[PDB]
Image: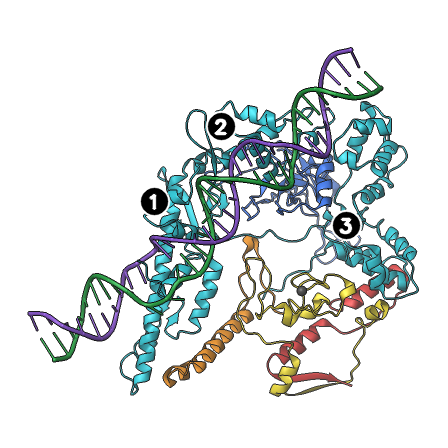
Chain colours: A red, B orange, C cyan, D blue, E yellow, F purple, G green
DNA sequence: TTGTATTTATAGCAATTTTCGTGCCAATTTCTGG
DNA sequence: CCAGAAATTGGCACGAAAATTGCCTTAAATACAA
């Protein structure tokens, strides 16, 4: 509903098709936070 | 794209805060590089650093 | 008699630089001379034509291959809604060897019926046919317009209106209605969704009319200036080393020379602008058609400079007037003679030709000979070939390509 | 305010917790009807590709959408407008000095006015309605005034 | 194959933990795609990003989808191509994020 | 007192290239009279 | 109706005018030492 770019489109397409299911995905604000923290000289990353 | 410019009426683009900080850092770094290459007196390079 | 020291050539080269280039050069010289110095929003996402097309594609029952073909087709659509590549390029971009040109044709035809209708058309004829295919059969002149669009469009663009009668076997009553129906369509279906912003320029000099006379002044928001760093200048005296003193003295000398050169450039530009404004005064009062035919030698004599200096100064500098923004070289033009004795500027002639063409009879547009005859009543005496050249410069079609059905 | 005939009693829960029950005669007599006035502004500026013009010739739109504009491209006084209606017609010039054969064909078929022109007209925002009661025009000194001014 | 290319840009990264540590200069250099050398942002004459600036297209990516800065390569058939004139990759414009 | 070094002041000349209006004339379009 | 005549258009050519571009380290004012 807020900030998953692919999830919004997939949910809208599924709703128009009568399939009430979602693929959650990853919020974009978390990626923005990761980039901002990396810009401070700190190595933060997701693993596995 | 995480630090965009401000497009306003009249074609003015102005600036953002992060962009201003980056510009100041880049200007200081370039001046220090040129002074170090030119073998400037230490009294000026210390202030530049 | 002029000694070309490598710094006089630097002062001369500074005249012909625009404000942006001058600022870049000032920054470059500023980062090398220590004694020189200078005195949350995020936005919104806007929907374009391609975003709308992809939104419609995602809500269309396509297969995976058809969806990839649709993505390729929507990618190659410009602002006006026309397909910018042949279908062979799309087929190559697909990268699969099991797809024929027919599937791409079917996908393109499906896409062409999106909103707006006629988008992703190959050319004007295809777009017009697509738009016409969505009309109900009750349209009074659908068939004649369809025939004209499908078969004979080149001679319709040539404004024949006579061979069209012979080939289509019609009359003026029906042909005019068919042409009006054709002209009622949308040549650019993709301009329904418009995005962007106009681009502006920052003038170098401003001219106003105050107390009944024209005043010219440099624009203070863009005039370049530099300043002497006093902190490092206070160290010019002995600092327990002779090399430091020599370095400071040389850099201070160079900085002072650069500041003097900048001030001289600004003064020269202001004087040239004042002379230009004084020479062309009727233009700022009554617009065009009153331009005087002045050249570089005319300005170079009122300021006691050389023609080369005037040529260098007036390069890529803009003047703002109550009429608009000009390039400061738009005021220099050629001339033709005059019956009463004098000269007429080519800008005035172009304006007069535009005004005369804009108010002619649509049934019988004026030719170049008629325009020359009309101009030879005010005492201009301009050649027919020159009138044709002016009309071509104005991008106005010839007489046989300007007539309507009246 | 207004003097209203009022009774203090519960009425079927329609005045539960500060709720107010109002008779239809109050609505019919327009005792609490108010007038609200909104202002919209359209600015024509100067660009590098010529100046923007306030004009009645918007080539892409139809004849009906220009029915409430006068000869100067401004909405009439007293017109009833709703969301999406054009108030002031303005065009932004787009400039290119090269004419491709497709552009030449378009200019020949549909005229040169449709080309090298964009649309930047002032329109009523969605969800806004009302009657045009006043129009004011401010023009820079030295610029020719239109008929409305 | 365009189908796999389109399917491979909507994939979801898999993870189960978050790691934080200090950044080495070599790590910082491996993060970057280029070096910023000039404080300019927009040319203000062509309204295009200046080279080696804070918005340079050679470093951070194209300003338009699948188009290089000069314009030699413009469509999806040239995806992944590095232009020899401007140095801008032919890819999506979201890589600037 | 003056001879000499240091600081200002010096943005023109003279080739060289580009643009100007306008004639020449073949190709293309319109017109008129039998 | 036909076709030749008449008119229209623009590419090419031409000399003059106009605009552009390279030049390479000078002379005169003035403060200071002898
Ligand atoms: Zn490129």
Please report contact status of discs 3 and 1: CB closer than 8 Å, yes or no.
Answer: no
- Please tell me whether mark 2 sits on a helix, a strand or a loop: loop
Q: Quadrant of ligand 1?
A: bottom right
Q: In this figure, which residue is indicated by the disc labeled 3?
A: C82
Check contact, mark 3 vs mark 2: CB within 8 A. no
The quadrant holding residue D124 is: top right
Neighbours of disc 1 within 10 Å: few (<14), some (14-19), many (20+): few
Quarter of the image where one finds residue C41: bottom right
Which corner quadrant holds the C terminus of chain C?
A: top right
- Which of these two is toward me, B34 or E31? B34
**Residue C302, can we see it?**
yes
Circle 3 chain: C
Q: Is residue D147 visible?
A: no
Cα–Cα span, label 3 and label 1? 55 Å
Query: In which quadrant of the rendered image does the N terminus of chain C lie?
Result: bottom left
For residue C68, side relative to residue B36 (left or right): right
The residue wearing badge 1 is: C301
| Precedes in sequence: disc 3 or disc 2 | 3
> Which disc, if any, is residue C380?
2
In this rendering, the label closer to the viewer, 3 or 1: 1
Q: Position of residue D41 (x, y in %)?
A: 58, 45
Asked whether mark 1 and ligand 1 are closer than 8 Å, the reply comes as no
Q: Nearer the viewer, residue F34 or A4?
A: F34
Q: Secondary structure at mark 3?
A: loop
- Residue at 79% over, 35% down: C182
Chain letter of disc 2 in the image: C
Secondary structure state at the residue bearing disc 1: helix
Of C118 and C259, the residue lying toward us: C259
Question: Residue C101's quadrant in the figure?
Answer: bottom right
Can you say whether E9 is above or below C210 in the image? below
Q: Is residue E88 left or right of residue F11?
A: right
The earlier-in-sequence mark between 2 and 1 is: 1
């Amino acid at each position: 509903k807020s900030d998953d770019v692919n999830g919004r489109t997939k949910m809208y397409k599924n709703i128009v098709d009568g399939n009430h299911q979602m693929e959650p995905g990853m919020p974009e604000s978390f990626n923005v936070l990761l980039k901002e923290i990396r810009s401070l000289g700190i190595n933060i990353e997701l693993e596995d | 794209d995480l630090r965009p410019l401000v497009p306003l009426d009249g074609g003015r683009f102005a600036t953002s805060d992060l962009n201003d900080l980056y510009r100041r850092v880049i200007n200081r770094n370039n001046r220090l590089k040129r002074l170090l290459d030119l073998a400037a007196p230490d009294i000026i390079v210390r202030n530049e650093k | 008699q002029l000694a070309m020291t490598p710094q006089l050539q630097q002062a001369i080269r500074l005249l012909q630089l625009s404000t942006l280039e001058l600022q870049q050069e000032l920054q470059q010289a500023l980062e090398s001379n220590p004694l020189l110095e200078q005195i949350v929003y995020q936005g919104e996402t806007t929907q374009t034509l391609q975003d709308y097309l992809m939104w419609q594609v995602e809500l269309t029952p396509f297969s995976d291959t058809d969806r990839a073909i649709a993505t390729s087709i929507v990618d190659a659509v410009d602002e006006t809604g026309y397909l910018t590549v042949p279908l062979e390029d799309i087929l190559e971009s697909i990268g699969d060897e099991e797809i024929d040109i027919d599937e791409v044709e079917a996908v393109l035809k499906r896409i062409q019926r999106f909103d707006p209708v006629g988008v992703a058309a190959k050319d004007l004829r295809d777009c017009l046919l697509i738009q016409l295919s969505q009309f109900d059969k009750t349209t009074p002149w659908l068939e004649e317009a369809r025939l004209i669009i499908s078969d004979h469009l080149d001679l319709l663009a040539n404004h024949d209106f006579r061979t069209l009668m012979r080939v289509t076997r019609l009359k003026e009553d029906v042909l005019k209605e068919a042409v009006n129906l054709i002209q009622s369509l949308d040549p650019r279906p993709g301009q329904s969704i418009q995005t962007g912003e106009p681009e502006y320029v920052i003038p170098d000099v401003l001219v106003r009319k105050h107390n009944g006379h024209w005043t010219v002044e440099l624009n203070s928001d863009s005039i370049p200036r530099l300043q002497i760093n006093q902190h490092y200048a206070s160290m010019c005296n002995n600092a327990r080393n002779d090399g430091d003193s020599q370095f400071i003295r040389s850099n201070l000398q160079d900085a002072k020379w650069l500041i003097k050169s900048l001030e001289s450039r600004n003064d020269t530009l202001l004087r040239v602008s004042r002379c230009i404004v004084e020479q062309q005064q009727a233009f700022f009062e009554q617009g065009e058609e009153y331009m005087k035919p002045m050249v570089l030698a005319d300005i170079a004599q009122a300021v006691e400079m050389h023609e080369s200096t005037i040529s260098r100064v007036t390069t890529q500098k803009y003047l703002h007037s109550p009429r608009g923004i000009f390039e400061l070289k738009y005021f220099f033009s050629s001339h033709v003679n005059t019956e009463g004795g004098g000269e007429a500027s080519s800008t005035a002639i172009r304006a007069l030709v535009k005004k005369l063409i804009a108010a002619e009879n649509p049934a019988k547009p004026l030719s170049d000979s008629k325009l020359t005859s009309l101009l030879s009543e005010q005492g201009i005496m301009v050649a027919r070939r020159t009138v044709a050249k002016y009309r071509e410069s104005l991008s106005i079609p010839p007489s046989n390509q300007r007539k309507q059905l009246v | 305010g207004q003097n209203m005939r009022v009774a203090f009693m519960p009425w079927n829960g329609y005045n539960f917790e500060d709720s107010i029950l109002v008779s239809e005669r109050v609505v019919q007599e327009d005792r609490f009807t108010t007038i609200h006035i909104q202002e919209l502004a359209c600015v024509s500026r100067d660009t590098k590709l010529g100046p923007e013009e306030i004009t009645a010739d918007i080539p892409n739109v139809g004849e009906a959408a220009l029915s409430k504009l006068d000869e100067s491209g401004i909405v009439y006084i007293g017109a009833e407008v709703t969301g999406g209606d054009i108030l002031v017609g303005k065009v932004t010039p787009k400039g290119e000095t090269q004419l491709t054969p497709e552009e030449k064909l378009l200019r020949a078929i549909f005229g040169e006015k449709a080309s090298d022109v964009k649309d930047s007209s002032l329109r009523v925002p969605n969800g806004v309605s009302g009657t045009v009661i006043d129009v004011q025009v401010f023009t820079r000194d030295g610029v020719e005034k239109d008929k409305r001014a | 194959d365009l189908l796999k290319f389109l399917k491979a840009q909507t994939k979801t990264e898999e993870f189960d933990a978050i790691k934080i540590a200090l950044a080495s200069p070599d790590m910082i250099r491996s993060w970057s795609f280029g070096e910023v050398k000039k404080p300019e942002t927009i040319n203000y004459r062509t309204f295009k990003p200046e080279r080696d600036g804070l918005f340079c297209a050679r470093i951070f990516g194209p300003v338009k989808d699948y188009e290089c800065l000069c314009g030699k390569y413009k469509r999806l058939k040239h995806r992944g191509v590095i232009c020899e004139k401007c140095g801008v990759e032919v890819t999506q414009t979201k890589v600037r994020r």
